Length: 431
Ligand SMILES: Cn1c(=O)c2c(ncn2CC(=O)Nc2ccc(-c3ccccc3)nn2)n(C)c1=O
Ligand SMILES: [Zn+2]
Image (cartoon, helix red, strand yellow):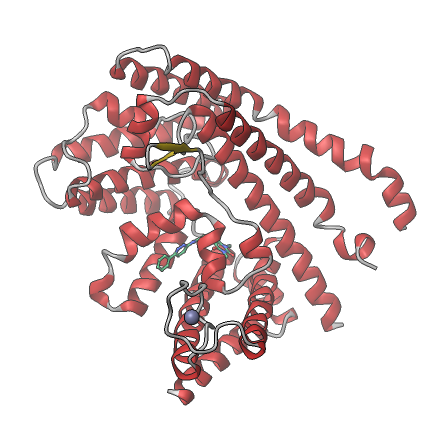
C-alpha cells in the first residue's frame, strides 16, 4: 500500500538510484574537470586538442568497452570525407551523405543491435558535429578547414563525447581558448548536477509510481500513459542536465555577451514541456541543441521542397539520428504532423482573432489586439492541455515494433491522431 511504499521509499529507490547514477558518471566528471584545469595552463592549442582526443578515447572506452571502434571509425571516415572535399562548396552535402550511409548501414544490422543501440548517442553527437562543421565551412561561418588535430579534438571533446549536447566548432574553439574559473561557472555545474540527480530520482521512483501512491477504464489507461510519459521526460531531463554539467565542467557552454560571460548553456527546458504552451515549444525545449542543429542544418537545407516537406525531412533526420525503432519513428512522424498542424492553426487563429494565441509568446511589440484577455488565456490553456494530451499519448510508447505501438495507441483509441486530424480539418474550414 501507500504506507509501506513511503516507509521504504528513501532506502529503496532514492539512495540506490542516486548512488548508481553518480557512480557511473563520476569518472567522466573527473576527466572533464581535468580537461578544464589543463586548458587553463596556457598550453598550445594543438596540445589541448590532443589532450581532449586522449580524454575522449578514454571516456569512450570507459562507457562502451572495446565496441568504441565504431565511433572511432566514424570520426576517421568523417575527417577523410572532409579532407577529400575540402575545396568544394558542398562539404555539408558530402558529409551528410557519409553520415546517412554510415547510420543506415548500422540500422541494416551489419553491426550488432545491442552494440549499435549502446553507443548511438555518441555516434549521433559525432555525426551532428561533423555535418555542422561541413555546413559551417560551406556557409563561411568557419573560415578555414581545420587541421586534423582540431577536427578530432572537436569530435572527441570530453564534455560532449558521451551524453554531451552538440556544440558548434566555434563554440568548441571558444572552450579551447579557455575562460577563468569563476563562482558562476561552479554554480552552473553544481546546479546542473543537482537538477540531473533530481530528474533521475524522479524518473526512477516518483514517475512510475505517481498515480497509485503520490496522487490520491479509459481514464486509468491515460493515467498510466501520462506517468510513462513523465518518467520518460525526466529520464531525458536527466540526460540533458548531465550533459549541461559535463559541457560546462569541461569549459564550454558560455556566452560572451556585451563583454560579460554567462554560463547559460541550456539543453532541456523541463518547465516548457511539463507545463507546455504548444507542442512546437515542447519539441524545441526537449533538446535545444538538437532542435537548433535540425533547424539550421536540415530544415534550412530542405526548404526547397516546401515547408511541410522540410518538416518531414527534419523529423526523418531526427529519426535517423536517434535510431530507427518503430516506436520512436512513429512518435517523430506523428510529431511532424502535430507540430505543423498546431503551428499553422495557431497562426490562422491569431490572424483571424487578432490574439496572442501563436505557438510561441508574442514579442512586446505585436499587432494583436487581444493580448491578456480571458479568451486569450482560455484558448492558450486549451492548447496547453492539448499539448499535455499529445505528450501522454506519444510518451505511452516509452514505458517493441509495429504490434506494440499499434496496441498502445489503440488502448488510447488513437486519440491524438484524431485530434490532430480534427485540428487540421478546423484549420482548413476557418481559412
Ligand atoms: C517531444 N519529443 C521530442 O521533441 C523528441 C523526441 N525524440 C526526439 N525528440 C527531439 C527532436 O527530434 N526534436 C526536433 C525535431 C524536429 C525539429 C525541427 C522541425 C522543423 C523545423 C525545425 C526543427 N526540431 N527538433 N520525443 C520522443 C518526443 O516526444
Ligand atoms: Zn501578440
